[PDB]
Image (cartoon, rainbow, N blue to C red; front, side):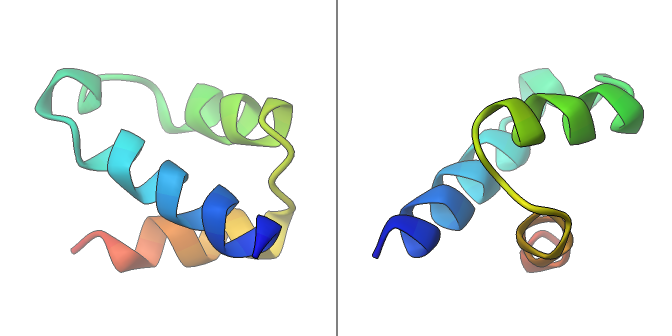
Length: 49
């Protein structure tokens, strides 16, 4: 599904060691800019440990 693709792509982005030091505020805006909702964003954040 389109939602599953959005969330799974987000998780993969977030797991990249190179993006760790990226401000969480900008991660939120970035994910919104890729079409994710607030609930999708929270789901993506918590799939990462």
